[PDB]
Image: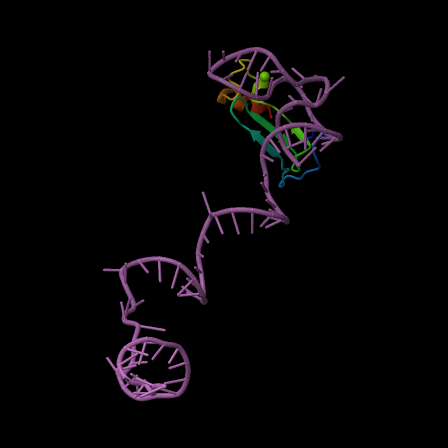
Length: 70
RNA sequence: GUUUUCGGAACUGAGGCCAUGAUUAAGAGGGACGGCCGGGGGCAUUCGUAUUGCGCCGCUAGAGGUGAAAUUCUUGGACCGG
Ligand SMILES: [Mg+2]
C-alpha cells in the first residue's frame, strides 16, 4: 500500500475475501485462487509448474512451493 | 260250458311307520374376509449429482498417466474455476 490502482479502496479494519480452489488430487496439485464469485481468477499455480521431475507433481514438496507463489 | 279273484304275476295311485336318512371339523388342504406388510411384478411419472461434449467468460503453461516413463491433449488457450 499503495499499489496503487490494483486492489479495491479498502480501510484498515476490514479485509477483502477470495477463494482458493485447491484441487489436490493424485499425480498433481492445483492451488488456483479466484475472486469471491469463482470465475475472475487471480493467480493459478500448479505443482507441476515448479517441479521438473514429472513424478513429484503431487508430492508435498511441490505442494507448498506452488501455494506460496499464489 | 269251464267259474276259475281261483295258484302266481303284471303295472299304477293314495298311506302309516322308520329317533326317519348328511360322523368329524385335522397344529391337512382350498377359499372368504380384516388390518396390515414387503428393493415382489408391469405401465407411466418425477428428481439427483456425476460423466462426456458444447457456447461463452476469466485465466494462464503445462495437463494426463505411471513404480518410472511414454503413446496422448496442449498459446486453436490444454488442464482450472463460473
Ligand atoms: Mg501428459
